[PDB]
Amino acid sequence: PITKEEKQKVIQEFARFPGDTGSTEVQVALLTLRINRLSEHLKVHKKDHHSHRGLLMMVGQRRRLLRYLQREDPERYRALIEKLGIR
Amino acid sequence: KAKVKATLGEFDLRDYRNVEVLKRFLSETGKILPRRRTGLSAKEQRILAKTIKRARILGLLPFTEKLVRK
Amino acid sequence: KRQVASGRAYIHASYNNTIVTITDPDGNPITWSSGGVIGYKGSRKGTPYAAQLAALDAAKKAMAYGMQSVDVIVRGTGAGREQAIRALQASGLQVKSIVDDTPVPHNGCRPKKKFR
Amino acid sequence: MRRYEVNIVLNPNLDQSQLALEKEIIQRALENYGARVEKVEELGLRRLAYPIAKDPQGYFLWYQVEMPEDRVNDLARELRIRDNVRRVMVVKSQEPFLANA
RNA sequence: GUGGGAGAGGGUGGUGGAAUUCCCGGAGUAGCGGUGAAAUGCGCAGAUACCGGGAGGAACGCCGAUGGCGAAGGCAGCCACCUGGUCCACCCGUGACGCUGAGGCGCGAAAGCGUGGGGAGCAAACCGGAUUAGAUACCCGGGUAGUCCACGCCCUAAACGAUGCGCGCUAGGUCUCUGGGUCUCCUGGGGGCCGAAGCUAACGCGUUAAGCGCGCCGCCUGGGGAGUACGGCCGCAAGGC
Ligand SMILES: [Mg+2]
Ligand SMILES: [Mg+2]
Ligand SMILES: [Mg+2]
Ligand SMILES: [Mg+2]
Ligand SMILES: [Mg+2]
Ligand SMILES: [Mg+2]
Ligand SMILES: [Mg+2]
Ligand SMILES: [Mg+2]
Ligand SMILES: [Mg+2]
Ligand SMILES: [Mg+2]
Ligand SMILES: [Mg+2]
Ligand SMILES: [Mg+2]
Ligand SMILES: [Mg+2]
Ligand SMILES: [Mg+2]
Ligand SMILES: [Mg+2]
Ligand SMILES: [Mg+2]
Ligand SMILES: [Mg+2]
Ligand SMILES: [Mg+2]
Ligand SMILES: [Mg+2]
Ligand SMILES: [Mg+2]
Ligand SMILES: [Mg+2]
Ligand SMILES: [Mg+2]
Ligand SMILES: [Mg+2]
Ligand SMILES: [Mg+2]
Ligand SMILES: [Mg+2]
Ligand SMILES: [Mg+2]
Ligand SMILES: [Mg+2]
Ligand SMILES: [Mg+2]
Ligand SMILES: [Mg+2]
Ligand SMILES: [Mg+2]
Ligand SMILES: [Mg+2]
Ligand SMILES: [Mg+2]
Ligand SMILES: [Mg+2]
Ligand SMILES: [Mg+2]
Ligand SMILES: [Mg+2]
Ligand SMILES: [Mg+2]
């Protein structure tokens, strides 16, 4: 799945500053990572519906955080979206 | 009557290969003993059941037995 | 014409009948009896007295074959499931051991509407 | 690569040529699928609780290994294809939960 | 975020034993089965019972609980892989990013439909045997669809805690599941049972509120007519809204 190696790689990649863990950018990054993992898990296993509900909730949370970022600072929002390739 | 854990050492509940101690937790038949006679907690019993099934599939513990004197 | 001198005895008891099969130490049968082998025809076959008479008749046929030492296997439940073993004990056959080997599934097949 | 425990129960009546052959075939299967062998315990002749393949006994093997995950099932299949191997149970390694501590 | 944890949560593939049925063989006679009694039925072409071997399908005994998981439907052999939800400790990061939610979209037991597989046991319809004033039923013997799998529909239910979601406040006692702790105990988070205040028409509810408050959604306005008619939408149809 997602081990601490890949997780820490992404976190240190998307940190606003050294030591930051829960920035909106990092939250959306880890969210999108698990999103892509699940959506590739749902390319196969079309009959896995509960994991699909989990994917729905993850999409919802990522979209809420992106809406918040767009409301607060649009430029960092554009940077994040272009960096992750969403929307 | 004595419960199994009361007369036993500091043994591994996750070792499916030790038939000597896993045999203590089976009944006269191949049935797994309830918690009344094993003296185990819920978690301990839940682990013991899976280890017993593992040992059964490896031909170490009997799936079922025959009752005597009936 | 066999002179077996030792063997097993299987008691299959139900709520409609009880039957006894006397066999040799490696599984092949020698004689047998039931509530219908003896006079009883209907539900009378399921009574403990019919089980006693069936066990005794099978035991005497085993005597004709020359049976002395007998191991007992029991499968099923019904009236006279025990009376068969009591008569088999007092029949003149030295009972080696009694065993209940009633086959019970691990929840494999769906029963009839009567059994649910 | 995760840690696994491979239990192998095979025919007991083998002599030394056959037994060494089957064991080296298991070794080649472990090599071909990337199974680093951490330790090995060979119990051998043991009295089974129920007959397996018409035989009341069996020969036992236990390998603690570290190998990639997505190859474990294919390795298990290739280990099962052998005729003399009657039982294959690959188990993910775990810590010794104790009782009556 | 970090670090731990429990679990029939879901999907995929593999795999184990018990039992039923069937087939091969051995040995073995005269019945078995079934019921309140019986009869149909099966058996001399050798049944039932017993032993060994083989095939196939379906379901997972003991563990098992008054237990656990899930949003609900619902989810129990074992193994591996893929994956969801959740809880606790640390007090680390962001800094109101929240709650609810018409519509929409997705899920949705069983039965039912379509195409193709599969088929042991069970079994609507049906075929017989009984019972009875009659038996179109209950009881017995057979037996098809179906039950099972793949894919696509169907969107119903006592889909029940007959109790929408979220948050805060308001005695405790007792049993329990799972974490943490300086571990007669305390502290979280779930599952029950008594019971303060209070509520209720009463039964009863009572920190798992049916109490005290707030936000938002759904629904109700006498019974029959009737979940019927017409209209629309959806559906292959049954039919549903
Ligand atoms: Mg009868
Ligand atoms: Mg093999
Ligand atoms: Mg599960
Ligand atoms: Mg599963
Ligand atoms: Mg035959
Ligand atoms: Mg005939
Ligand atoms: Mg006839
Ligand atoms: Mg005929
Ligand atoms: Mg077939
Ligand atoms: Mg139970
Ligand atoms: Mg998980
Ligand atoms: Mg802080
Ligand atoms: Mg700050
Ligand atoms: Mg919501
Ligand atoms: Mg809606
Ligand atoms: Mg449905
Ligand atoms: Mg269905
Ligand atoms: Mg169909
Ligand atoms: Mg039937
Ligand atoms: Mg009639
Ligand atoms: Mg019928
Ligand atoms: Mg309300
Ligand atoms: Mg503790
Ligand atoms: Mg729950
Ligand atoms: Mg509590
Ligand atoms: Mg309580
Ligand atoms: Mg009062
Ligand atoms: Mg109460
Ligand atoms: Mg409340
Ligand atoms: Mg009220
Ligand atoms: Mg209405
Ligand atoms: Mg009116
Ligand atoms: Mg209707
Ligand atoms: Mg219409
Ligand atoms: Mg139309
Ligand atoms: Mg209707």
Image (spheres, rainbow, N blue to C red):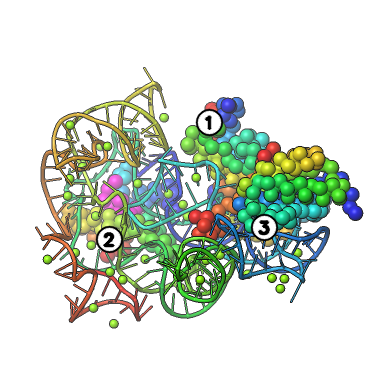
Residue A26 part of the magenta segment: yes
Quarter where residue D98 is shown: top right
Foreground mark, 1 or 2, reads 1
Which residues are the magenta region?
A: A22-32
Q: Secondary structure at mark 3?
A: loop
A20 or E188: nearer the eye? E188
- Mark 2 vs mark 3, CA separation in Å: 88 Å
In the rendered structure, the answer to whether residue A47 lies left or right of residue E87 reads right
The numbered disc on residue B39 is: 1
**Residue type indicated by callout 1:** Gly
D49 over A51 or under it: above or below = above
Foreground mark, 2 or 3, reads 3
Residue D50 part of the magenta segment: no
Badge 1 density bin: few <14, some 14–19, many ≥20, Cα 10 Å: some
E235 or D65: nearer the eye? E235
| Chain for numbered disc 1 | B
Residue E49 screen position, x and y as percent? 71, 55
**Residue type indicated by callout 2:** Ile
